[PDB]
Length: 113
Ligand SMILES: O=C1CNc2ccc(Br)cc2N1
Image (cartoon, rainbow, N blue to C red):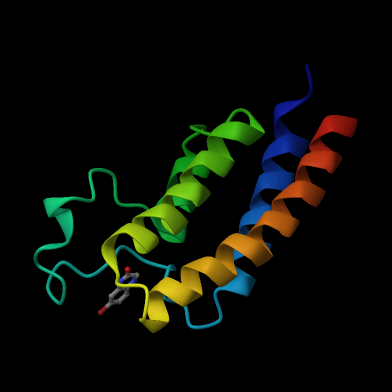
């Protein structure tokens, strides 16, 4: 029960803040199937921030949970694919932690709308 434009403005700002936590930019674009050709063998729905931006502008995120779901997919795919002792796995743990705080604050703002 809110206006669309300010909500999407909020989601754009939030997506920017999540990308800011991915300082290595390892989640900015789809996992390169050229360098990881077996990636799709158990990752049923790849996700990344560029795809999220396209989903956002295509009006596919009309509530906070659908936006947060795809962010969680970025995290969960990375934990699933990579061994625990890798930089990638620890980066997803850190993104889960730092992104979670970004998301909680953003959701508080959406709920005021
Ligand atoms: O799981 C991942 C996350 N992103 C990524 C970027 C480049 C390369 Br190479 C591998 C990965 N794997």
